Amino acid sequence: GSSGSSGPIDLITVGSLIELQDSQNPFQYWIVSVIENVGGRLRLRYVGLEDTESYDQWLFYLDYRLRPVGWCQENKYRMDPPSEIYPLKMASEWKCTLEKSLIDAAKFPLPMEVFKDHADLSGPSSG
């Protein structure tokens, strides 16, 4: 493990399930699971590809893409993986790991504190 300063780094622990956005598909999102945490370096990996270690992704808890699992359950804008993997596996294989994962998040969920932020949230304005 690793015990550094007192912050969000200690709050997050390998395995923690979190949501991520797509560079190309902003409206679309997917569920990932923390593979490893190196001083804030959370190596996310689209659920289902646990076996393979090529289509992984590394990011810091200080990112905007990192979102809590459950928000998409309010609007459900669009919950689907990237076409870079979607085809790699069977639609069923993507839905299987998707569901099972959802539950896990409810068993090993992280404290909001982790994503404790705030900024201009006022309604839009015509221009």
Image (tube, rainbow, N blue to C red):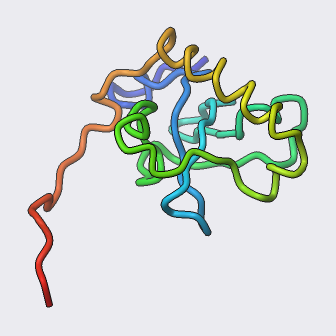
Location of the N terminus by quadrant is: top right
- Please provide percent x and percent y for residue 80: 64, 47
Q: Residue furthest top?
A: 107
Residue 22 located left or right of residue 125: right
The picture quadrant where one finds residue 94 is top right
Q: Residue furthest bottom?
A: 127
Residue 86 located left or right of residue 45: right
Tell me the residue at 41%/49% (across/down): 62
Residue 61 located left or right of residue 7: right
- Please provide percent x and percent y for residue 96: 75, 25
- Please provide percent x and percent y for residue 88: 90, 48
Tell me the residue at 55%/23% (across/down): 16
Tell me the residue at 17%/57% (across/down): 119
Q: Nearer the viewer, residue 110 or 102?
A: 102
**Picture layout, residue 57 above or below residue 72:** below
Location of the C terminus by quadrant is: bottom left
Tell me the residue at 52%/33% (across/down): 18
Q: How many marks?
A: 0
The picture quadrant where one finds residue 4 is top left
Q: Nearer the viewer, residue 50 or 6?
A: 50
- Please provide percent x and percent y for residue 21: 54, 54
The picture quadrant where one finds residue 10 is top left
**Picture layout, residue 62 above or below residue 70:** below
Q: Nearer the viewer, residue 77 or 112?
A: 77
